[PDB]
Image: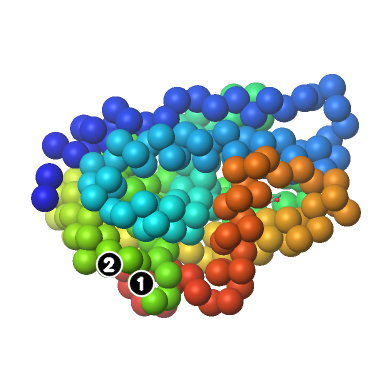
Amino acid sequence: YFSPVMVLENIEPEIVYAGYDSSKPDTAENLLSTLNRLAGKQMIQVVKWAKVLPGFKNLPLEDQITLIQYSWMSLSSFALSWRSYKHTNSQFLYFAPDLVFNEEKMHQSAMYELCQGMHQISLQFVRLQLTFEEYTIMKVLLLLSTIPKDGLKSQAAFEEMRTNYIKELRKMVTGQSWQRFYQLTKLLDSMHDLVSDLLEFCFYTFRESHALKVEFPAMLVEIISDQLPKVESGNAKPLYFHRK
Ligand SMILES: COC(=O)[C@@H]1CC2=CC(=O)CC[C@]2(C)[C@@]23O[C@@H]2C[C@@]2(C)[C@@H](CC[C@@]24CCC(=O)O4)[C@H]13
């Protein structure tokens, strides 16, 4: 099918600034609009990364779009946990160098509980001493973790790619290694529940954005308008390593 982990380490997207205006009041609307703007900028980086991801090009365009749209909150939250771990030892939420959340910002954002939920994942990175090589493979697995309930256009092509990256994770964890592999698959599975709550809040603010004064960039409007009716109608199928 394929040293893909070496390629993953090298294609990691660069630093994305939030463009946070600290001279503006820290209302929920101002913080959430900055977070949405940062998400749009990161989503362009996700598309550029995916294009050069080994095996991703073999999937038809429709499937590439489906995977990117279904997984955007997963990839985004996992990278946030990584940045938080690497740059603050998971003491804060490192959204961007110019936007680091402390307790004050967690409360002001009107997402305190969702923020604490995120902080728990970054705290697991500390507990496990997650490595950069493990992180990069796991991020690919999150891109491939949610599919249509009736499957993709080229389901066989997708399963081959996913299976091959799971094999890369197993080779990477290796004096006993099975223990580590299951610790990593348990972490990946726990992302689906967190992502459900994050999407619930995102969908809510999207449905009445002006009413709440929350701004969405064009990129997020497009993704969310497509994703929201699919997720809410049960057309999304989260893939679990270990059925709950
Ligand atoms: C703790 O929340 C988050 O951090 C997640 C993950 C994430 C990490 C990043 O590093 C980029 C930003 C995103 C995508 C995100 O902050 C934006 C704003 C999102 C889309 C939010 C879930 C709900 C919200 C709030 C307001 C809205 O409309 O939806 C995301």
Q: Is residue 109 left or right of residue 71?
A: right
Q: Is residue 154 left or right of residue 146?
A: left
Identify the residue shown where x is 24% and y is 50%.
Answer: 58
Identity, as a three-letter code, of the amino acid under mark 2: Gln
Q: Which residue is mark 1?
A: 151
Q: Is residue 199 above or below residue 14?
A: below
Identify the residue shown where x is 67% and y is 36%.
Answer: 37
Identify the residue shown where x is 65% and y is 42%.
Answer: 218
Q: Which residue is mark 2?
A: 155
Label 1 Cα neighbours within 10 Å, binned few <14 / some 14-19 / many ≥20: some
x and y percentages locating residue 230 in the rendered image: 55, 69
Q: Is residue 21 left or right of residue 117?
A: right
x and y percentages locating residue 211 in the rendered image: 88, 54
Mark 2 near mark 1, Cβ–Cβ under 8 Å? yes
Label 2 Cα neighbours within 10 Å, binned few <14 / some 14-19 / many ≥20: few
Which part of the image, by quadrant, shows the C terminus? bottom left
- Identify the image quadrant of residue 179: bottom left
Q: Is residue 126 above or below residue 98?
A: below
